Length: 207
Length: 203
Image (cartoon, rainbow over all chains, first blue to last red; front, side):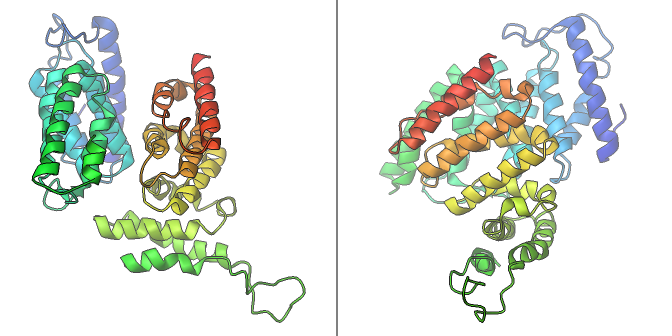
């Protein structure tokens, strides 16, 4: 467990951590929606929690876009570490949600794309308000006033106008707060793109 | 380069007027090996360029060019190129032309029939893409959805039960406009796909 961005060293570190998360789980427990913040009394992984968080963060983000196995294992270990009962603060899962959303809008690589989708969906089923606040609201904000625009995620990488709709279709399938607020906001945007804009396919896709 | 990529299908097509037809022998300088040869000359460079490219335009060009080349060449006749083709193969599953759609669906069929490590490592990525293919869309024809059903069946057969159990409910849920669409072979085969997915998950 030493900081490393090399594909081999970081990959072996992550696949090792994949067994220590399982040992920690078997020894202590897993998340419940009531135990989202409750930590276990004592362990040595808490002393190493900052190091594993940092190595996972640099394994997914602040990393090259060509990493398919590295980023897939990164989001997988992020999700598995989230799966522990209240051992990561809402700040940590917020950072993880932001990482997933940024790396899923930036890269089209369906490996990292669908792995980030899986991570975001698991966060949604284990953290309603967190995902709805960071990922869902941002994604609803990327879409503009007028239809048929380039959804500029950043200076260069952009997604389609229907990419937001597809992402909305992906999760919120079982998240009450997410799905209700999403229905409300999609109705709001339907009204807006019909009133201040003149579009048909966007209204059709939204409805 | 975008126009060249979209026009690049021309190099590999049937002629129906200049081949070594029965009877005629003075038809042309016919060579049947043009397809495969052209693929072997194009694919490799294309894929290297795609993995060495960043943006919307040039990567879309590489995908469209390699897809428009692979669509006319038989997928089972181009085997060594499949391994490096798998990334662009997975890429070519979302674009307007149902021609590239049927071609890439056929190519994943052949790949998952031959390759299994790629399929096992990429199932968590391919499955929702095939789901979006099976969804009704301005680009998903009824035939396209039928082919997505066929690939879903083939990948569920090839992938072991471990991952297939994790991808039963999504296929069962996101197929309701396919067993109720305008055509009925689409409907019958979606009913069969739903039933086979249900029986594979329940066992």
